[PDB]
Image (cartoon, rainbow over all chains, first blue to last red; front, side, top):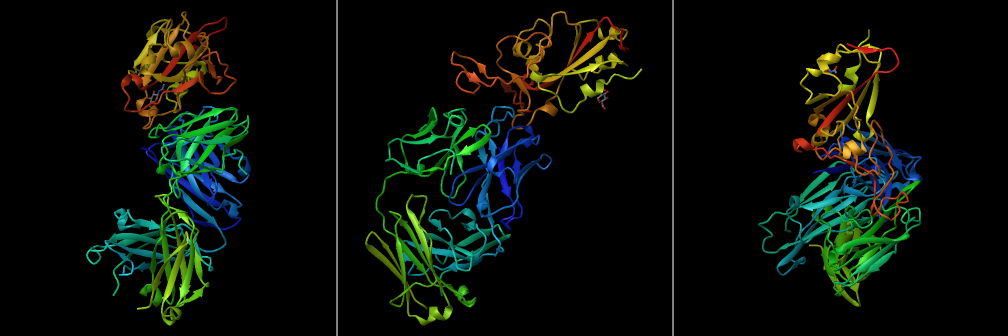
Length: 229
Length: 213
Length: 194
Ligand SMILES: *[C@@H]1O[C@H](CO)[C@@H](O)[C@H](O)[C@H]1NC(C)=O
């Protein structure tokens, strides 16, 4: 079954070139379909960028035509996107997707519907540098205990650009996990927190480890949260 | 700003049926039958609900359905549920211009038991203190409506410096949640006998306190 | 006495869709048809003029080489007097045909994992094709009273569909490359002999 995955630089300098690639697996791009890029500025609407099929033919959104190139490399089985002269209006989550229709000659091919979507990679356009997150454990205590339940967490402090994603115990702790939106500090660096609610009886016996991933650098920090002294 | 005009919000009550419209011109919607609807839940990738006007992808509930008349497309959700609370975007081909989107429409499920904020306040961890920083973290969750005021107190006097608070955000349970952080020097954490976070919502206030050692 | 470039039709990497069948004109060259007939790597080699061994001793003013990809089922339709979606809307041999019809299985090359959608065939056409005609139009077939106005709709269908070749398909649904060799003789000296 087909899978799409975007990768690329988390951060880009203003007026330089944004360069993301999408690696297909489970289906040879050359074998059919159109393949497209669609972006979503933070808290704003979907924008379609461009599509391409294996020959190299392209269709582009008129407002971004002068700055956009989409390429295909069939030997690596991936398609890529470059966008030049970036501004803050290019700060966005960038998705790659596959079309509904496999026939490449259908009317409005690659400009109809998109069936299979990637997770999305985010790109922030800024002059600031990337900073790695620092991870501090928010320990369980008798004040955070509430009867049978109890709350512990992970504070992810002074990182940039977005995003950070947190999973707990390698994805076995999923329920009661809330991971809050980040706040922007005066320094310019983001911070955010992840809290989970856990059985109070099990606090000394059970293991709780938060898995902070910050893909703009290449950091992944796993912090063990233990009860207080 | 969007060449397809879509109502900013729409709502319905559970069990009932809600319809979102999407108007373009005779050169997009009115011109071709390549009209597509997507459903995006907060923080997740868009999902295709409807292609080629009324055609349903596999795995999409029959409750969803779309249609079109003239310049205006419609997406009708029957048997409205809480899991349907999301943003919906419409799309269509535009000839010379290609693949234009609508601005989107937020759909609310309108079942709204008023909830109260649960508050948990974490003191500066000992790791942070050794790095010569101190951060108070007050976390606010599971509260409806999505309306909240946070005040911090040092001892009993008010504090307005270094407070950063996130706008409230929708969870999976369609309730809301927000976070407030107090940035502090470590000597300040040790000077004052107690810090406290007060979280007001619908007149009543929940206040939690942390104290050094 | 140059050699006929039969290799560049048969062994070509890329083959055309039946609806836009390729034609190559052969001339001013000598060709050994007998190596072709005895290859046995062709699953199909029917001739409707004279036996393949005898035309080795025959001259022609021109040899036309038509190439395309179809399904196993449809190979029988590449013949004179044959009816079917291929023979009526895609490629029709006349009944006076004097040539050979050659094919081999291309599952290894032309079938892909999620379906290959490059190869098309014409699903709807208003009239049956005349012999040796080629239609590549993309006008929307009108299958109902409602006029199509050029827009895909209900009873308005894009006139071409695709074999979605998968290597797991049964034989009959597997891709077959086809080469049709038509031998023409005009009031002009011959340029293709053996
Ligand atoms: C196709 O290639 C094979 C191997 O190179 C060769 O033996 C054969 O003669 C070629 N076919 C033609 C028609 O030249």
